[PDB]
Length: 137
Image (cartoon, rainbow, N blue to C red; front, side, top):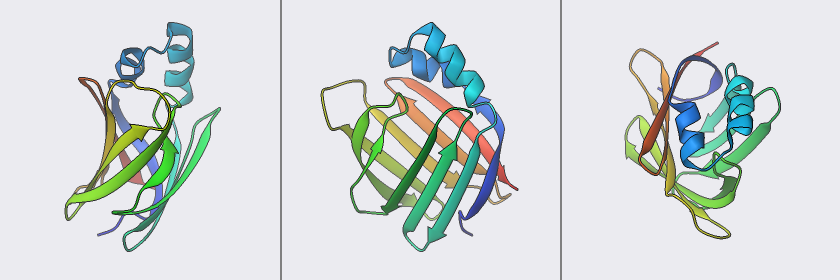
């Protein structure tokens, strides 16, 4: 199995709390939760090399990485970070993030494919876990 495709969200849990624990103000949180309610997610996987584009109503990020090699991206609250993805198991990658500037709560993300073809995206900030689930278009 593999991750390539266009993915549409089917479940989202705890996203506002994730932003809240990173100090995001209520006005910005409300805007962000609504903007991300139906994101466009596109993944192109070539072996261990990934391209991932995520677009909300007001923001669009593009990341390019190979498993095991550091790359620059942003945290969920928009801070530049150096990231590193490893395979935790066959279907599941986990990313540790380190801020380029300053300090803050520990943040990470994981992406896992299930046998039924779902993509589970987990983001952690401090002690808060946000889970989103997607299916292929």
